[PDB]
Amino acid sequence: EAKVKEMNERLEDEEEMNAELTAKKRKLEDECSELKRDIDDLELTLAK
Amino acid sequence: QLEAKVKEMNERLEDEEEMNAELTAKKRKLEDECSELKRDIDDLELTL
């Protein structure tokens, strides 16, 4: 009965850890998109 | 019955824990990529 409840809890935690770490990941995806455009557009005004 | 209940939870934990394992490995490379993109800028801005 114990290992049953214990594994229930961990499941809810892993299901939510999925959501959490992906919001962390996403913030880095967003950043890595933006930083690239800021690299590029700077050079896109610098270029000759 | 309680061992069956034990089983599909152990099993589903393995699915979940690997999704979560992926999200942190995906997270690593994105931290690293952000790193170098942030570099490319801060080097380049030292002439503006």
Image (cartoon, coloured by chain):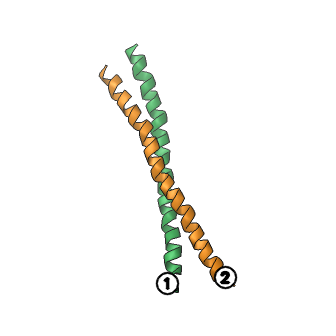
Chain colours: A orange, B green
Q: Residue furthest right?
A: A48
Residue at point 46%, 42% (across, down):
A18
The subunit letter for the residue under badge 1 reads B
Q: Position of residue B25 (x, y in %)?
A: 48, 51
Residue labelled with disc 2? A47
The numbered mark at residue B46 is 1
Tell me the crowding category of disc 1: few under 14, some 14 to 19, or many 20 or more residues within 10 angstroms, Cα based.
few
Residue at point 47%, 36% (across, down):
B16
Q: Position of residue B22 (x, y in %)?
A: 50, 46
The numbered mark at residue B26 is none
Q: In the image, is residue B1 above or below residue B36?
A: above
Q: Position of residue A34 (x, y in %)?
A: 55, 65
Please say whether residue B38 is visible from this viewpoint: yes
* Labels 2 and 1 in the same subunit: no
Could you say whether the residue bearing mark 2 is in a helix, strand or loop? loop
Count numbered badges in the picture: 2
Q: In the image, is residue B12 above or below residue A34?
A: above
Mark 2 vs 1: CB contact within 8 A: no
Could you say whether the residue bearing mark 1 is in a helix, strand or loop? loop
In the picture provided, is B4 more to the left or to the right than A40?
A: left
Q: In the image, is residue B3 above or below residue A43?
A: above
Q: Position of residue B48 (x, y in %)?
A: 52, 85
Residue at point 44%, 48% (across, down):
A21
Q: Quadrant of residue A40?
A: bottom right
Q: Amino acid at mark 1?
A: Leu
Please say whether residue B24 is visible from this viewpoint: no
Q: Residue furthest left?
A: A2
In this orientation, which residue lies closer to the viewer: A48 or A10? A48
Q: Amino acid at mark 2?
A: Ala
